[PDB]
């Protein structure tokens, strides 16, 4: 019952994902391959949010579908709830992907 | 249903707007046209909050009605929920305007 | 109805007050009159929380009843909701007072 | 009734504990006895969260059961609600312990 509150975390990951992948500073950085700017635009967020991890991705999936969702992977030391939202340009084309991760022990 | 929870974000934007536009440090900076102080009093808030963007405005609307509200603009890559609250002096005169933005993909 | 949600803010101020006035680093600083340490232990919290203001006080009320509560002052540009909790030593003696402020336009 | 909302704080401590003890940067630091990295990976969190205190521990309990829970100690100046979650390796072996503390006056 208390653990069933995955949506407690799941919804946090979702919104957070939508917001982080929507930031113009990140949108700019992702386009210009400014891994430096990206690094300075996420590190703070880590300690800020109670998110186990955060990840910025490229259109191909490289390690710097118009729809946002929540991923749930179960196995070993609980399960990981990771919200995911795409990074769009002014035309909507998927230029990247944000994946904020969470954990429920 | 899960998306219908715009008030989830909308209420965050509202309160945040009321608070940010109420800060004395910002009130001081907005009056003295201290764009420098303003810049150092908002940048942190960006990474802090899950707000897509934040904006400080002047009485005229320049880019540094006694009532606060939420704005909703729909079109292209979801919709943007932006809470808005005026910046007042000790007399209540509208000296500025804060507009915290959010996004729902 | 939406505005009636003062407890939304009021409860934030309350908890925040209890926590900030409970921190050992602040407890230490308040005792040793380390206004410097106090200054470095509150400034971050300002931008962090959506609190209009935050205040540390002395047992007398100086500007650096075993019970916590919420204060509500109405007039001019909305009302100010300020949670208040005392700073205790290891014996419970009131050595200070924390007053986190909020605003509802 | 308002005070009975310990789960308000208790649940915050729980999740926060699960997340902080799950961070790879901390997992790495705890294994390599990198008290320096740990120090730079927790200090921010202190001011960030409304947590009275935060603590990282070793498998033995040193001061740097596969299950997470909430601790409640009552006495003198209210009670302390401290969420607790273990630090695991890629095999699940308990390598540490995180204990985020809270207070209810």
Image (spheres, coloured by chain):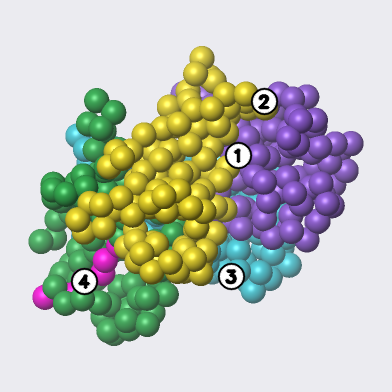
Chain colours: A yellow, B green, C cyan, D purple
Residues at circles 3 and 2 in contact by the CB criterion of under 8 Å: no
A44 vs B60, nearest the viewer: A44
The residue positioned 26% from the left and 69% from the top of the image is B56
**Residue A40 locus on image (x, y percent):** 51, 66
Where disc 2 sits, the SS reads: loop
Question: Which chain letter goes with mark 1?
Answer: D
Question: On residue A76, which mark appears?
Answer: 2
Front tag of 4 and 2: 2
| Residue stretch rendered in magenta on the structure | B54-60
Does the stretch in magenta take in D7?
no
Q: Is residue B11 visible?
A: no
Question: On residue C39, which mark appears?
Answer: 3
**Residue A58 locus on image (x, y percent):** 42, 53
**Residue C61 locus on image (x, y percent):** 55, 63
Q: Is residue B26 visible?
A: yes
Question: Which chain letter goes with mark 4?
Answer: B
Question: On residue B57, which mark appears?
Answer: 4
Front tag of 4 and 3: 4
The residue positioned 56% from the left and 45% from the top of the image is A53
Between the C-alphas of marks 4 and 3, the distance is: 29 Å
**Quick check: do tags 3 and 2 share a chain?**
no
The residue positioned 89% from the left and 36% from the top of the image is D60
Where disc 1 sits, the SS reads: helix
Q: Which residue position is annotated with label 1?
A: D19
Q: Residues within 10 Å of mark 1 (few under 14, many from 20)?
A: many
Front tag of 1 and 4: 1
């Amino acid at each position: 019952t208390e653990e069933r509150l995955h949506y407690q975390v799941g919804q946090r990951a979702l919104i957070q994902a939508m917001q982080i992948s929507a930031m113009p500073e990140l949108v700019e950085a992702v386009q210009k391959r400014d891994l430096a700017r990206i690094k300075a635009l996420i590190d703070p967020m880590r300690s800020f949010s109670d998110a186990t991890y955060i990840t910025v991705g490229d259109a191909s999936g490289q390690r710097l579908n118009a729809k946002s969702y929540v991923s749930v992977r179960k196995g070993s030391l609980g399960s990981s709830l990771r919200g995911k939202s795409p990074i769009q340009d002014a035309t909507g084309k998927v230029i990247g992907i944000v994946s904020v991760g969470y954990t429920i022990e």
